Each structure stands twice: as C-alpha cells, then as structure tokens.
Image (cartoon, rainbow over all chains, first blue to last red; front, side, top):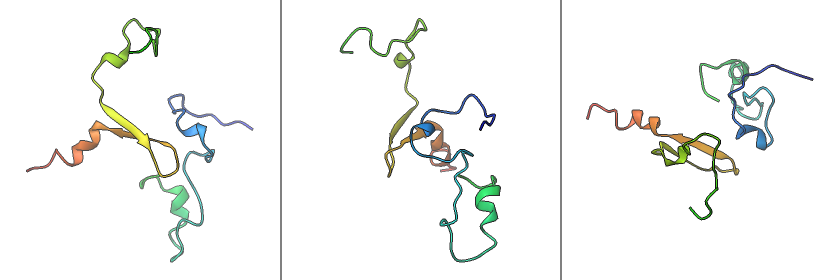
Length: 48
Length: 48
C-alpha cells in the first residue's frame, strides 16, 4: 500500500517503531471521560 | 578534527563551521530530541 506525503520529513522518526499516520493515536492514553477520545486522533489544534 | 575528510559534505564550505543554534539528546526511550534555540522565546522574551 502507498500514501503520498511531504519530502521534508526527517529520518529521525522512521528509525524506530512508529505509526504510519505520523499523528500518534491510541486508546490507552486517557481513561476517565468519553468525549475526549475523538480528538486524540482528529484534533491538530492541540499537540502530538 | 581527527581525520581530514570526516563529515565532509559536497558543498564547498562544511556547515559545521557555522555557529551552532541548537542541541540534541536522547529521550526516555532512546530517540533523538530536537531542542531549538527559538524555544527561548518563552523565557528570555519576557517583559522582565
């Protein structure tokens, strides 16, 4: 499978195990409320 | 240097000569961190 991407992304990130979207996702990253999960993926106003 | 020909780049002036504007080090897992001088714009850029 293939996906287009920019050319000025560094090799720092691709030497260790990581996620192909570049935006680190997950479900173990919060566990008290419910309205806070969709933004762990679909919010770039915040930080990675 | 130790050996004339180390980290030599194709460009006519080895950019290592120029003033360094940052520093890198290892994180909690073993990945390179990119700490840039511009991060001082939150501490030295104060009204004080």
